[PDB]
Image: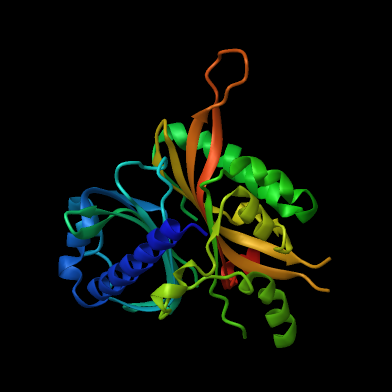
Length: 132
Length: 183
């Protein structure tokens, strides 16, 4: 396709990989600092249970059992201008398996939308779904 | 089963868009008629995370999705375009090669994540049956849609919204024992 769309898709793929790597290491290994990755006013939806704004997101995570995530699938699209213009946005899914403390092993799909504060990418939305 | 709702104004857009779009994807014969939702700037990817565990049957049926699937986990950043379908013609072209399905509408979990006058972000998690033109296959799936709202220009000067899909991902995966139980 167009050599600039190629550049936009490829840039997005690198960001999505850097972000998800660090994100999934923060939830498993440093949940104390998990809030730092959300915008002040982000939406979280953990299995259809909403948490709006970091303060409230940041206390959902502190009340969740300890976790270990195995990633297997990563996907990122750059978001079309009209969906949210003047802020370039990435639509990232991560899927795999997760082991919560004192719970059966499960599968998960996590779908973020991220934008940039300065040089750092943070969550605008996050939809988490467990399966097994 | 819990559904998330952004805004209570978005409520009857779940049934209107998601449950009409899904029903019309179902029969692959009339699936070309989804050309209307997509635009010149539309983007579609397909991901497949199905752990195989009737093994030859499974792998030949899942290949229908896999042959188009995209995954950047451990991939070389140059091949990042591999799997990305761009523009209405190209998207509908991939969508017409996928198998026939029947979604289990009772199984569907909804997450509306944004909603305004410009548009919405809407995710569905559910169970569908993959059907052959050989045997039936239950699959897990996710569909995520970034959609925009544009004033339809019928001639009556009454404001109306046409839905367009800007971003689109189908995800194929294992059904959960609970869904299989209750299909």
